[PDB]
Image 1 (cartoon, rainbow, N blue to C red):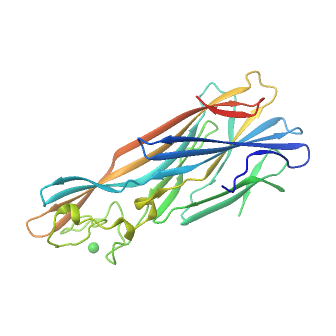
Image 2 (image 1 turned 90 degrees about the vertical axis):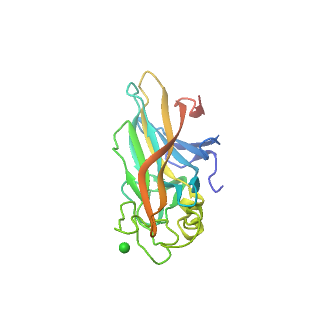
Length: 281
Ligand SMILES: [Cl-]
């Protein structure tokens, strides 16, 4: 892509060594790309590591069940989560993360720079490193989760949605006749439940296709520290709700159980600050 790998001198006796890693999780419908950047400033007491987490999480919007023509279930992704976590015994600390706060915009973007003070600062502080964050979240919201020096996590959760001019609806919508009409195609149509689900092409590309995260986590590591190797766990995660259409005696009625299924993908990475390398275990 536009993300280069290699080593550049970004000035003031500072080097940016960048590499990449890829792991396919075909079971969970996940391609998990990681671009890492070692910012080694000879004038700073700490080496910096930017872990740009990328790839694709397929939405896997699909009809999973059918009981005659009066009942059917639907699995739809209600949340995409990326998390990074450092075990407790480690010396390394999470100094910074992007997005830094909640993002309600359908598009997020940020260009990461190094300010030669040991601080990575995002704008949308002088010279750029090779990363410009960009991701899209139609009908979705981004939320930061319990950030500490040992764990950071982003949660891209479903917000609201217009349903062929009926909407807007969310996971909590209710109607005394039709219940939750989120993905309900027709209110009184004559067809099998399996066929009365909204076309995913008429909705968020996070539902039909999927979500492509682009988050940066910054890790600081003291040079004088004894143990100069570090483990870090990176988790990609999909939460899928269960939307069921049941034919009542008169009309169609929808229900939505939250967070019924959660598919969790996890990889461990060895960080070597001296060799400035990142590898899978
Ligand atoms: Cl209504």
